[PDB]
Image 1 (cartoon, rainbow, N blue to C red):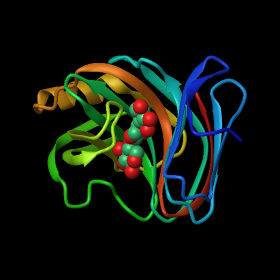
Image 2: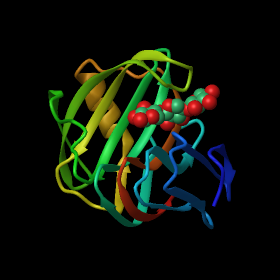
Image 3: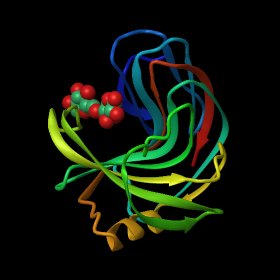
Length: 189
Ligand SMILES: O[C@@H]1[C@@H](O)[C@H](O[C@@H]2CO[C@@H](O[C@@H]3CO[C@@H](O)[C@H](O)[C@H]3O)[C@H](O)[C@H]2O)OC[C@H]1O
């Protein structure tokens, strides 16, 4: 397993962040593979990808994802100027992260319709420190743990709806969890 932090592993950028609560282990495997095992964890986010990401990347992911409680499997990343945290959610556990969020449209991509939403984080942690910033979401209706994500279809739909992205920071396939349990093994390319 590895310490929380960022870096490169077998050619892929990785980010593993947690709240220090314990109960979660993250491991970097060969190529674009990573595994997450958690049991009564706290808040955490980890996965592999790129730094920086691009606005036209076709991301391939494959493996298993078995959450028991609150967790998401997503293409996840950020932009700067404006600061935006974004998600293309392929699967989740007990909580749909768009619950209560205002719907801003639909986009069809890679075999499913996705619902689009915008939320706001107020004085929360970010890649640039504590801040208030928006979050963009595409939530897949047809849940899966393998597939291909044509990021451009999402970024373009978001733009069309008034959700613009700044300069890309990291872009990864991530397993996020919030006080839950589970296991996942994902390969990115
Ligand atoms: O040391 C700093 C890092 O901690 C920082 O990392 C990012 C912090 O925000 C993370 O995003 C939130 C983590 O908490 C969850 O509950 C929220 O849902 C996520 O929005 C992000 O994943 C980290 O990369 O980056 C800057 C460093 O200086």
